[PDB]
Length: 12
Length: 58
Image (tube, rainbow over all chains, first blue to last red; front, side, top):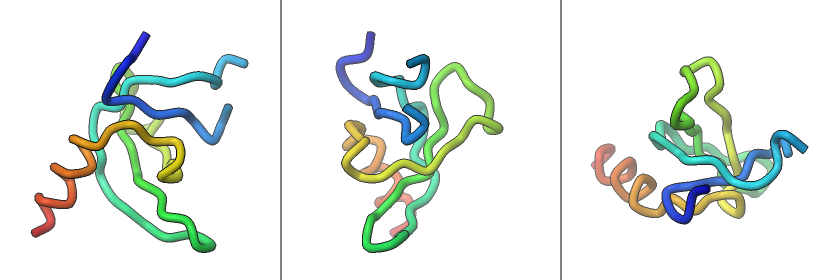
């Protein structure tokens, strides 16, 4: 599961 | 549910402003370009990719 270089989706 | 939480970002490709919010156009790791999305700043945790993108533009 990512801990860096990541983002959450508007779709969620 | 399946779109919740966080996913690995591969690339930051562009920036825009919508209704007072800055969004970045993202390529997601493991996905094709067809799945690229615009996401608001508050959704992001990819500061090295954002920096690289802005530097690339001058």
